[PDB]
Image: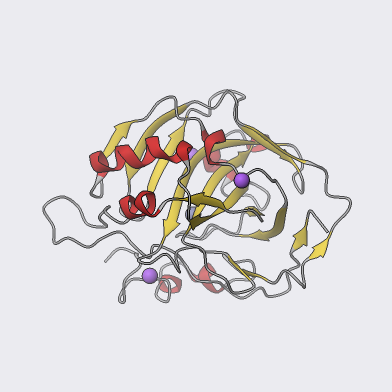
Amino acid sequence: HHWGYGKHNGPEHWHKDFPIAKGERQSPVDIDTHTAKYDPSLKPLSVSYDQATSLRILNNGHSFKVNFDDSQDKAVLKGGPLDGTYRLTQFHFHWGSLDGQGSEHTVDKKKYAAELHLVHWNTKYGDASKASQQPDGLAVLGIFLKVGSAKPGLQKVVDVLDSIKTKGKSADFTNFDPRGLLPESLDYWTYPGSLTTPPLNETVTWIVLKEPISVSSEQVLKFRKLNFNGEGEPEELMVDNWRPAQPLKNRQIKASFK
Ligand code: NA
Ligand code: NA
Ligand code: NA
Ligand SMILES: [Zn+2]
């Protein structure tokens, strides 16, 4: 009886195995754009992805994930709310059964069709496992997806999904450039939060970009052909793999822009 997104194992059940699910710094949250305070001292955000080296893509039964070779000082996030340097290790997505839902964060209660999470670890902790345990160990760059015009840089991802349809499948996935997934603006909101999947560790600085990327209906439809199940099991489409907004509790969301 593994955690998932269904009626009997979904987000409302997670707290039994992972009591931190009811903690003080859980993610995602609704971003109240009127309450968020512009912070004129945030340093400029620096997203330096030109030497990123992708390795493999996987269906883990909960999302699809592209892992990067993070053994060297390449693809890094710094500045903004962050102290030091955070190294990209993987990205994955959350998406809906319909275009009107799928994101984890919301903006004034608005749900986007999907959300991209680029996950980075603080290099002061040596690798991602140790970093994942520290209160300032991880930084996730979150990017909303809306349905409209195609995102050309997503197409190479979309086209490999047929090869990882079911849980447990993986494939080599080299030379993917995550710069092709970024919007024009780096305007963002930031707050202290958690992983949005078990174990829900409260170790993430969230940086959520204001500007969504547009992807086509056809691109997101291909996400929805993935399966939660393993090969040979009854087909359950991988859709609505998003955790809803959690209580903000005492937290402040800061804006990088006026
Ligand atoms: Na990792
Ligand atoms: Na853009
Ligand atoms: Na769900
Ligand atoms: Zn995620």
Asked whether 158 or 122 is in front, the reply is 158
Front residue (pair 10, 1)? 10
Image position, residue 226 (x, y; %): 27, 52
Q: Residue at 22% of width from left, 63% of height from top?
A: 236
**Camera-side residue of 114 and 82:** 114
Nearer-the-camera pick, 185 or 232 = 185
The C terminus sits in image quarter: bottom right
Hey, which quadrant is residue 66 in on the image? top left
Q: Is residue 169 visible?
A: no
Residue 189 vertical placement versus 18 (above, below): above
Question: Would residue 153 appear left or right of 210 to someone viewing this image?
Answer: left
**Which residue ends up furthest to the right in the rendered image?**
41
Instruction: Give percent across and percent down for residue 68.
Output: 47, 32
Residue beneath the point at 60% across and 30% down = 49
Q: Residue at x 55, y 58 (%)?
A: 201
Q: Position of residue 204 (x, y in %)?
A: 62, 53
User: Is residue 211 shown above or below 24?
Assistant: above
